[PDB]
Length: 104
Length: 138
Length: 87
Ligand SMILES: CNC(=O)[C@@H]1C[C@@H](O)CN1C(=O)Cc1cc(C)no1
Image (cartoon, rainbow over all chains, first blue to last red; front, top):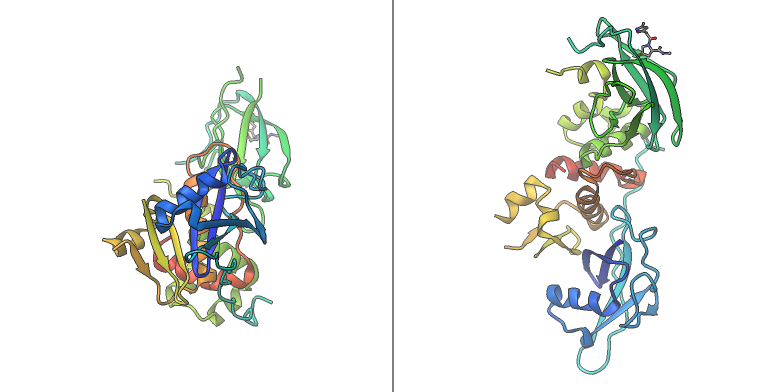
């Protein structure tokens, strides 16, 4: 079963899919190929919760029911500068304008 | 030209609405005139007595947006080997058509010309889906 | 491989090259694995990227296709981007 995700760090968003049976570590290898940072320099999160490497995406709560193509699930990403991991931080998207008079 | 064949050969059909829309089944009569039939609520089915060679199409009852039936536009009841299944579903609309549907659902046609968008878009909004226009075909 | 789509407000969206090639306008803009959209904000571009995944997942599927959701607040701007990108 495919799961559809948004891997987010600061102002970066990766749109990718993975298998429910695939691991957190395997997702880190995907991030590696794109962002050129090894898995040991990466931390993955579900909201504020740090995800363990050997855990499957399904076990982490990424299911077909919740990680849909038209509404993908968010995975937080943090990088380590040296030594010391940076705090998880995701820049929010822009705010839509006020609904025009004719739409309300 | 696009019309039902008067075969007089009964064909039992099940209209299966596998869409979140209220479905309007449309029969193309012997003159090629679209004939509307009772609407189907979102997750429901209906047994209908139709005929071999008859032409059907399905639209959203409120907005007339085009729907698919057995992955195509037209459904033609065939010979009952018993009843023929007509699986009505949403097509994968383009992002543009999907946007126009949402904007049309929120804005009264008198007010399309009040939206701050390019002129070509006012014309696209006013060009509502229509069975008659779709009937070309061709 | 992957391509980068940058919003007017600096958000960088990394999507599969095949998914982005769904847009004829994007296909033309890449032909240099980064595209800047000076007029498309992130709350719109994120939805465009969800559309690419939705389209690739559900095109020629035979099963049940769900509705592509659009919040009323995003509709106008998403329409303008879809019209430009020929999405
Ligand atoms: C209740 N079933 C119907 O109304 C069906 C559906 C469509 O096939 C046209 N139709 C008719 O009876 C009209 C008709 C009679 C004969 C005989 N040939 O056509």
